[PDB]
View 1 (cartoon, chains in turn cyan, orange):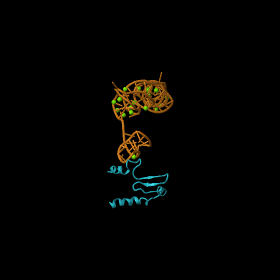
View 2 (view 1 turned 90 degrees about the vertical axis):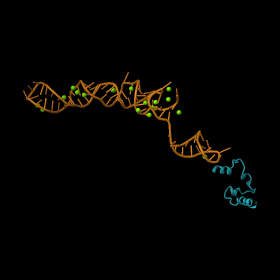
View 3 (view 1 turned 45 degrees about the vertical axis):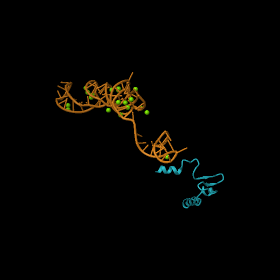
View 4 (view 1 turned 90 degrees about the horizontal axis):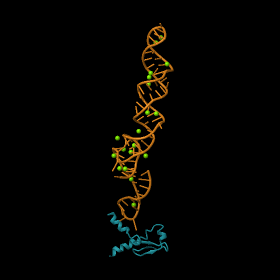
Length: 67
RNA sequence: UGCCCGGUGCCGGAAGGUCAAGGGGAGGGGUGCAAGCCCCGAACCGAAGCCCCGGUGAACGGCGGCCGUAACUAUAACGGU
Ligand SMILES: [Mg+2]
Ligand SMILES: [Mg+2]
Ligand SMILES: [Mg+2]
Ligand SMILES: [Mg+2]
Ligand SMILES: [Mg+2]
Ligand SMILES: [Mg+2]
Ligand SMILES: [Mg+2]
Ligand SMILES: [Mg+2]
Ligand SMILES: [Mg+2]
Ligand SMILES: [Mg+2]
Ligand SMILES: [Mg+2]
Ligand SMILES: [Mg+2]
Ligand SMILES: [Mg+2]
Ligand SMILES: [Mg+2]
Ligand SMILES: [Mg+2]
Ligand SMILES: [Mg+2]
Ligand SMILES: [Mg+2]
Ligand SMILES: [Mg+2]
Ligand SMILES: [Mg+2]
């Protein structure tokens, strides 16, 4: 049960697939789940980020809530 | 038909260590008035065997443990001791 679960979360698609992509050219920290793109790589890939997960947490309520 | 000759066996080894009878007689003892007679007795010389030095497995025989490490977990080619 620990290998059936973990194999899904990591995803063999570690070439380029699921969650986020971090631009170091122009600094576009993007999460393809929703869309929200921003330049906070300096403030995120060098510190905390508890507020930029909020839309991923808020858009995931209205995902479940509205249906 | 692999690897191990440290132990055992067998094989080789005029060195060395130990080694019995025998040789040797520094020195000591018994007795006799005595010449003497008799008895212990160190050094040193003195084999095989053993020690020792090597060889030998289709001679007797013996051919490990622990720990970590790789693209999901597993496993561990790899490392450490
Ligand atoms: Mg071998
Ligand atoms: Mg042997
Ligand atoms: Mg032998
Ligand atoms: Mg040897
Ligand atoms: Mg034996
Ligand atoms: Mg011999
Ligand atoms: Mg000799
Ligand atoms: Mg003698
Ligand atoms: Mg004599
Ligand atoms: Mg004699
Ligand atoms: Mg004398
Ligand atoms: Mg006397
Ligand atoms: Mg006298
Ligand atoms: Mg001899
Ligand atoms: Mg054999
Ligand atoms: Mg042979
Ligand atoms: Mg045998
Ligand atoms: Mg043996
Ligand atoms: Mg591992």
